[PDB]
RNA sequence: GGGGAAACUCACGAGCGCAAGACAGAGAAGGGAUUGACAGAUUGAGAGCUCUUUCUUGAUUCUUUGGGUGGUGGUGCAUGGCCGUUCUUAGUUGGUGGAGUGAUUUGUCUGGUUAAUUCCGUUAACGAACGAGACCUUAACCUGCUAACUAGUCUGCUUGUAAAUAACAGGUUGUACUUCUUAGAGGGACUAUUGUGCAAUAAGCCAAUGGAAGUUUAAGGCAAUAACAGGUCUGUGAUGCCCCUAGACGUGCUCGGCCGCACGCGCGUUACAAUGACUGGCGCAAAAAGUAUUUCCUGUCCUGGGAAGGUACGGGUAAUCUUAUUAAUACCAGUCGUGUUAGGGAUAGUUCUUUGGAAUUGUGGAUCUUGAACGAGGAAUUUCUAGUAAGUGCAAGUCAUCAGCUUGCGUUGAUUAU
């Protein structure tokens, strides 16, 4: 079967899931089979470019990384991509490099943001009856 | 007269305990016999029927609701066998709420 | 809201009472010790008891 | 196969079948203490176990009520004679069954036997059979044209929590009088039975009970090098 | 009051039909009780309803005298059951001791502490029961376990566009695999670690660090003692008593009515625009449903400018099919330019379509028109602390058709207090 040089990490925010696969070579980032350039709301593309600029391109020119994302809505999706990418490099440096590098990129990243290696525990709240939402309730008449 | 027959066992139950009893003694029993190959328990997603009902039989003013659930657990087990072995592995007592469905695809 | 209840403190008293020689400053040890030693119907319960009992081990190390 | 039915729609239909049976049996079986019904379903058959206090009246005089019942289910659903099977199973402990006991006080109250005495008789019976605790509620006109509600407790009782659904057994009956409907609930908290060995009580202990188990001193022989 | 009522529902109203008036006593009936019905009138009505007209039919019974069914008729102050509310507040009991002749009291408390009569401690009280807690359900952690063609990954083959061991896409594949996805076992959190932080160093609180998670993790379910003549005879083949009983308050049919408008009071949808409206472009959800075989979800395909129609090819009683999609805020262009303006669309008039025997008193939907109030709201006053408010769509219940409601589901995501 010839076990590949693959590493596979996942990333999560709300209902969104990102699976990033990392293999060695000339660095690509393709999300859902397309460059980061084309990710829908333009503003938060820099969110995905963050861990890249934080680690420096030097780590990323050595690796082709492809991230498929399926999930909730645009923003959470962006955060999932973020996450998967970030802990993806870490997993690579775990298997194929020394542990030391894994450690120092871990620290490197988390000093900037912890949302990269750790998932946002928040999810939606179910709705309580007698309201238009998960707390707020039908208006009341006292007098 | 060799028969290679793929057997599909689908278990459905409103109680979980019952169905895991069934499942796990089918797996236990099938492995215990040499002619047998077991594609293991396949756990379908759990079906939850909800019925939300207003409590008071009247309009009596506070609105209270009842969240009434019925869970249906569905399992699949696959076997590589002949007829008699099947009838051997199905030979044990099962709790009442269990549905057992058997299908046979011939294989050459 | 972290105030601990009757059941838990009675429990912890007993667990130390009989077992003090077996017991450690480590929660994770004492919880397993408890589990072996006793009938505790809940994971959550056992853990609360073990934590308080640990707490009391530490309080015992200091004095009466 | 017969018809391909919605696992959801089938299962709900099975539950509704079960409930129709329970209403049918509690209604037509009203004299012998009727507790429960257990239904196994075979492609061949449908097996119904009627769990009851007085199986003898389920059968009747050489299957008068049995044959009647079996044929009732037959005409009702339509069934082959090999397709339906009815068993009656005894409840070994009558004191642990609510529906039974409420039937008991139904009976005693019909004979004009006074309230407190009857309530006491059953309660004493229930605890005599090992139930930790019991309570009875009688509501409606007792004294006068103005409704009263009388409670009788003895022993140990839980109301709130998931343990409620486990340890507490409840039944109600409507009791008929010239004056109207009066009504009666029986709550028997069952005991805790640690072994599958018997049909008793509750298999899983109250989440409250916490027990420390003091150490033992036993036989110790060592193995030591001899000295000469 | 699942109280979204076109018929039905349905109790209301106008006009018509049946008996499903059992059972017993008396008389009548076989030489006839009674049923039915062409046709002409009649009627709203092919209601034989009535009237004329006779032919059928063969005890299924008719007239009285009793009397039962049946009753969405009355009575919740006759009642069960259930359900609201005090109240999710923290309360409430008893035994044995102590105090009062006694009703009663201590227990059940000065004080800390907790969300909690939660605990600590005080202690003539000691021990206990209910309630709180425990518990249970959902959500959040596992690159470890158990496995999966009704999930996916990879591996090796291939296909297309390309110079292609590039890139992006398909199709296949296996004694392959578990990250993603199901979901079973077991872990995990105990307020953990630290703290010359506050605590009379006791319960506990606080902070920092670690942590998936430290508001009782979050959101719920359950809810003692006692009440309140709270609500419910219209949910019940649970009923007491009262009433209606053949032009009936029984069971049907036809047309209305509950939607009737000078007004008063509640929930609410939509707006008063530039953080906007409109015209394009854009492979972002979750959770629910689904066929007693053509009827239920519906995917292709075709016709129509459109709502919608074909029936041409098909799948799915469903992790297989509708679909792992088809949502809408959001984003990118472009128009429009602070004025009752395209903001805002109420109200109206033609046309077309769909559900239904039935749409008139517009069931919904489509196309042109028509375009009102409203320029951010008096006295008052509601709900709400984090994936929370708010905006934003989606489903489910209802349901042939009808969501401005309800019950849920995610998306975008705050201000301000702990
Ligand atoms: Mg909304
Ligand atoms: Mg109305
Ligand atoms: Mg009556
Ligand atoms: Mg009527
Ligand atoms: Mg006393
Ligand atoms: Mg005394
Ligand atoms: Mg005295
Ligand atoms: Mg007091
Ligand atoms: Mg005490
Ligand atoms: Mg809670
Ligand atoms: Mg009143
Ligand atoms: Mg069509
Ligand atoms: Mg759909
Ligand atoms: Mg019109
Ligand atoms: Mg309209
Ligand atoms: Mg529909
Ligand atoms: Mg409604």
Image (tube, coloured by chain):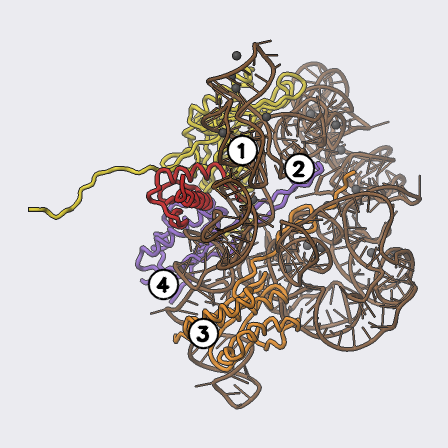
Q: CA distance from mark 3 to mark 2?
A: 60 Å
Q: Colour of chain E?
A: brown
Of the residues tagged 2 and 4, which is closer to the observer? 2
Residue at the spot of label 3: A6
The chain letter corresponding to red is C
The chain letter corresponding to purple is B
* Element type where label 4 sits in the image: loop
Report the chain holding disc 2: B
> Few, some or many C-alpha atoms within 10 Å of disc 3 (few <14, some 14-19, many ≥20)?
few
**Image location (x, y in percent) of residue A61:** 51, 81
Q: Is residue E31 left or right of residue E173?
A: right
> Few, some or many C-alpha atoms within 10 Å of disc 1 (few <14, some 14-19, many ≥20)?
few
| Picture quarter with ligand 1 | bottom right
Front in this rendered view, residue A112 or A86: A112
Residue at the spot of label 1: D159
**Image location (x, y in percent) of residue D47:** 45, 40
Residue at the spot of label 2: B56
Of the residues tagged 3 and 2, which is closer to the observer? 3
Beta carbon of the mark 3 residue lies under 8 A of ligand 13: no
Of the residues tagged 3 and 4, which is closer to the observer? 3
Give the quarter of the figure containing the C terminus of chain A: top right
Q: Is residue E377 left or right of residue B53?
A: right
């Amino acid at each position: 079967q010839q076990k590949p040089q693959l590493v596979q990490t996942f990333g999560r925010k709300k209902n969104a899931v990102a699976v990033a696969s990392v293999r060695p070579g000339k660095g690509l980032l393709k999300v859902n089979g397309s460059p980061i350039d084309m990710i829908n709301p333009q503003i938060l593309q820099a969110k995905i470019y963050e861990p890249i600029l934080l680690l420096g391109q030097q780590k990323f020119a050595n690796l082709d990384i492809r991230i498929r994302v399926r999930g909730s809505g645009y923003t959470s999706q962006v955060y999932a991509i973020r996450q998967a990418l970030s802990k993806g490099i870490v997993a690579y440096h775990a298997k194929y490099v020394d542990e030391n590098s894994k450690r120092e990129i871990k620290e490197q990243l988390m000093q900037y943001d912890r949302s990269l290696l750790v998932a946002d525990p928040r999810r939606m709240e179910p709705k309580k009856c007698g309201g238009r939402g998960a707390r707020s309730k039908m208006q009341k008449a006292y007098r | 007269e060799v028969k290679k027959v793929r057997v599909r066992i689908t278990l459905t139950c409103k109680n979980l305990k019952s169905v895991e009893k069934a499942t796990s003694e089918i797996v236990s029993r099938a492995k215990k016999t040499e002619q047998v190959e077991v594609k293991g328990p396949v756990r379908m997603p759990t079906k939850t029927l909800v019925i939300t009902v207003r409590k008071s039989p009247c309009g009596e003013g506070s609105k209270t609701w009842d969240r009434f659930e019925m869970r249906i657990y569905k399992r699949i087990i696959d076997l590589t066998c002949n007829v008699p072995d099947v009838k051997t592995i199905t030979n044990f007592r099962i709790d009442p709420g269990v549905e057992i469905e058997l299908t046979m695809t011939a294989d050459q | 809201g972290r105030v601990r209840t009757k059941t838990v403190k009675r429990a912890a008293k007993s667990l130390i009472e009989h077992y003090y020689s077996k017991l450690t400053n480590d929660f994770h040890f004492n919880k397993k010790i408890l589990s072996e030693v006793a009938q505790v119907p809940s994971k959550r319960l056992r853990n609360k008891i073990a934590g308080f009992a640990t707490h009391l081990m530490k309080r015992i190390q200091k004095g009466p | 196969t017969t018809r391909a039915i919605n696992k959801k729609k089938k299962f709900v239909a099975d539950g509704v079948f079960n409930a129709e049976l329970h209403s049918f049996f509690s209604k037509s079986l009203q004299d012998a203490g009727y507790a429960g019904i257990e239904v196994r379903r075979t492609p061949t058959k449908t097996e119904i176990r009627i769990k009851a206090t007085k199986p003898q009246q389920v059968i009747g005089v050489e299957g008068k009520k049995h044959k009647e019942l079996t044929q009732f289910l037959q005409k009702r659903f339509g069934y082959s004679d090999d397709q339906i099977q009815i068993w009656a199973e005894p409840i070994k402990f009558k004191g642990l069954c609510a529906s039974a006991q409420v039937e008991a006080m139904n009976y005693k109250l019909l004979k004009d036997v006074p309230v407190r005495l009857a309530a006491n008789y059953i309660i004493k019976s229930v605890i005599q059979d090992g139930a930790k605790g019991c309570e009875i509620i009688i509501s409606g006109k007792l004294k006068q044209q103005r409704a009263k509600t009388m409670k009788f407790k003895q022993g140990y009782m839980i109301c709130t929590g998931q343990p409620k659904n486990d340890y507490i057994d409840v039944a109600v009956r409507h009791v008929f009088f010239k004056q109207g409907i009066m009504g009666v609930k029986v709550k028997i908290m069952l005991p805790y039975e640690p072994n599958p060995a018997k049909k008793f009580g509750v298999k899983t202990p109250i989440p409250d009970n916490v027990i420390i188990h003091p150490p033992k001193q036993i036989t110790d022989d060592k193995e030591i090098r001899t000295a000469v």
